[PDB]
Structures are given as structure tokens and as C-alpha cells.
Image (spheres, grey):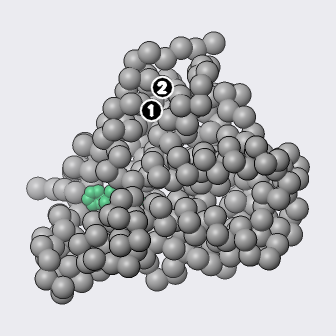
Amino acid sequence: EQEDVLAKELEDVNKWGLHVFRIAELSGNRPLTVIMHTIFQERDLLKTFKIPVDTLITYLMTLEDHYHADVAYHNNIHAADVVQSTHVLLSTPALEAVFTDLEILAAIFASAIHDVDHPGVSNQFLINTNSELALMYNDSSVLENHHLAVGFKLLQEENCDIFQNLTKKQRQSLRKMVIDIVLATDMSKHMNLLADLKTMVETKKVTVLLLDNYSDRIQVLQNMVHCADLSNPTKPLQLYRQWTDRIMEEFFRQGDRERERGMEISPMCDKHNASVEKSQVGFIDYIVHPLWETWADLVHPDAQDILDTLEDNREWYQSTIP
Ligand SMILES: CCn1nc(-c2ccccc2)c(C(C)=O)c(Nc2ccc(C(=O)O)cc2)c1=O
Ligand SMILES: [Mg+2]
Ligand SMILES: [Zn+2]
């Protein structure tokens, strides 16, 4: 009877503001797994890419296992969330039939792994602490590079290769795409990504959106997953505040070590100069709203509803200030 109620909630997989935490619990902490499975089913991807179902579950389960249950934000639930968000984003009327099946798969898949094996501290933290990871990747997109490496390496476990029936050309192309996307989730590439998104809205054409070259398509996709990645101030409030509590719990833990090692405690990593609300408003006025406002223009007027809520949410966090 608890698979019934989970089935009931999964009917919302096409809606923005899906109850993803309820889904987490109602599935035995298998949100990324059930949610990926429902999306592939809904989009017919198993049939299109001849992915055996046995193979699909194994893989998602192993992937999901490689999210850390003990980091509050960058876990399987967040992974589940971005995935589902990108999926809805994919479906916006203004993108109808712009993207191939294989382009679609990359964006969903990449969303699925974009933070796999995240340790719960930031790139900058890992660079500062001369960490084993940061030494590996020469201080450059340290974590993103990592999530990709892990996401790809898992395909190699017994009965995990969900790409086995793609052609060689298909595999090359999807590998590149997934790499180009996950790497674009590095928060220091934000300003440049967005500036590029702004030129594209500046010189866009319609028919529905028109793009005739890899580099225009991959950009849109990268920004789409960036949006999904940075999509939680745009969900209904009860959801977004839980996400805040969480990332904040993760940061405070970082700064407990940042203050412990004795570096200068990051900005907004100090549980004693917590300005949580002030920091969402700022995060929205300078990062999230500029971003979404822009995406909403590319797909005018499909994202209108998402942008409204965003502004209801901000106007709420502000109400909590003085
Ligand atoms: C709950 C919503 N929220 N809030 C903040 C936010 C928090 C405090 C101050 C300023 C911003 C952040 C941040 C810090 O950027 C969110 N997401 C992130 C995305 C990417 C990275 C990254 O290291 O690559 C980190 C976090 C976020 O989801
Ligand atoms: Mg990330
Ligand atoms: Zn993320």
C-alpha cells in the first residue's frame, strides 16, 4: 500500500514543485532511483536506447549508493531533484522537438550524476586544504570533474552499462555532451555561461526555438541543467525552505572545519554570523533571478510561473529581515 501512494506521488513527475522529499521517504531513500526509472519510462528511453530494465535499475542503485547519506544537501535527494527539474524544463513548449533523443538522454543522465560522491564541502575548500582531489585535478573544476569520473566509472560495474546498445558514434557524442554539461555546473563558470545565455536570447530565432549547431545546443542544455541545479528558490516555499535548512546545515559543517583548520571562514559559512535569510535574498538578487529571468526570456513565456514563485519566495525571505 506504500507503493500505491508512491505511485500516486509519481504522477506529479511532470509538475514543477514535485514533493521530492516525500518521494525520498516513501521509497526507502531511493528517490534518484525511482525518479530516474519513471522519467525513462515516461519518455520511452528504455525502448529507444534498448536499455534492459534489469540494467537500468542496477546502475541507478549503484549510482544512488555513491551519493553520501551523511551530507545534508548534496545527496541523492538533490540529485533526484535536479533530474526531475531538467526533465520538466526539457518539456517546455518553447523547446518542443528541438532536441534529439540522445541530446535528451545526456541532459537527464548528466543531471543524475552531476554531484555523485560529493563530500559536502566546496571546490574552494578542497583547494585550500591541499586535498587529494584538488591535487588530482589541478584546482580546476575539482568536484565536477570528479562527479563525472565516478558517474562514468560506475557504468563499468556488472550489468550497469545502460549504454551498451548505443552505437559507437552515439557513445562518443553522449560522453562529450555529459562532460560539457556536468562541467558547466561549476559555480565559477556561472558568470560566463550566463553572459553567453544573454547573447543567445539577444539573437534568438523561432518557428518554438531554433538552433543549428552543436555549440548552440550544448549551451542551452548546460544552462538548463545550471537552472535545474540552481532551481530551488523557484519551487513552492515549503520545499525551498527545507533546501535552505539543508545547504545551510552543510555549510555550517564546512566552516566548523574551516574555523578548525584555521583558515578564514567562508562567507556565509559562519553559524555565528549566519545571515541565512539575508543570504537567500542576495543569492537570488545576484545569482538566481538574473539567471532565471534570462532563461524565461529564451522560452517566453513558458517559465513565467517559475519566475513568479521565485519572486514570491524572495519577497517572503525579505519579509523576515528587520
Ligand atoms: C538552498 C538554495 N541555495 N542557496 C545557495 C546559497 C547559500 C548561501 C549563500 C548564497 C547562496 C546555494 C549556493 C551556496 O550557491 C545553493 N546551491 C549551490 C550550487 C552550487 C554550489 C557549488 O559549490 O558549486 C553550491 C551551492 C542553493 O541551492
Ligand atoms: Mg555540483
Ligand atoms: Zn547540484
Instruction: Kindly identify which residue carries mark 1.
Output: 295
Could you tell me if residue 50 is visible in this image? yes
What residue do we see at 25% from left, 42% from top?
Answer: 285
Could you tell me if residue 121 is visible in this image? no
Q: Quadrant of ligand 1?
A: bottom left
x, y percent for residue 125: 27, 71
What residue do we see at 20% from left, 79% from top?
Answer: 258
Q: Quadrant of residue 159?
A: bottom right
**What is the quadrant of the N terminus in the image?**
bottom right
Badge 2 crowding class, 10 Å Cα cut-off, few under 14, some 14 to 19, many 20 or more, is many
x, y percent for residue 117: 51, 73
Q: Is residue 78 above or below residue 215?
A: below
What secondary structure is found at the residue carrying circle 2? helix
Number of marks present in the image shown: 2
**What is the quadrant of the C terminus in the image?**
bottom left
In this orientation, which residue lies closer to the viewer: 73 or 307? 73
